[PDB]
Image (tube, chains in turn yellow, cyan):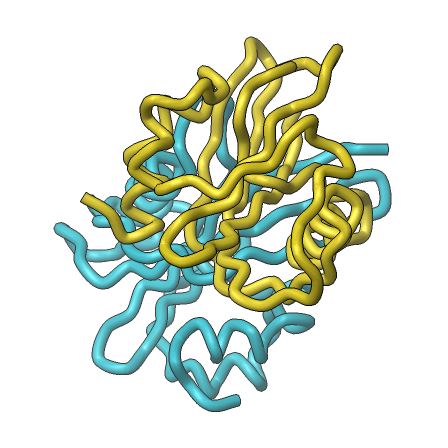
Length: 131
Length: 128
């Protein structure tokens, strides 16, 4: 089976937004880009706009598709679509995550990130125009 | 319900034209399903080799769209293909055709592709 997921790159003076997953979460304490699952009927952009509102309290315009990655957890596949988010109203707040931080994208390496995300870190850097 | 089939499709571009294959008949972009374990780019290179007999360099991810078939969700990823070794040969399709992208407007293409044809033109840098 496959699970499609969307994630947004929001930037602030070169830095990028990450959220720390809340207590008793599947990846409690690990740092990720905001986003979530695509629901039946939704375009990936519709899903991401919804998730950014639900997670961050912002109304975001979804920009260009930058990257798609797969990972496997046994017989289940995850397909993640990463979009550039250039424009939004409001400032992100930790409605879902236990903390939000704006980090230098080079920082991602040394952060406590999901094991599955580290494996695609080089593609993320390339998509973000790095190294 | 949460049921999904990820699919990859290639825009093979040469001399202002694009490659379409006639289904075993609607005209589709070459590609296929992503198998668990592989990257979308690995999946597309594999399918292009299987369907067409070419060794493709998978280029820029251009577009992603979702469509429904009732019980099942389809998510299509479209990658541009500019470079490949070998010549496309109809191993899977009953016919392959190089067409001007303009012709898409009046060719029997899958409902899902028709729905998003404007997005396809944008993704090719063409005006709709």
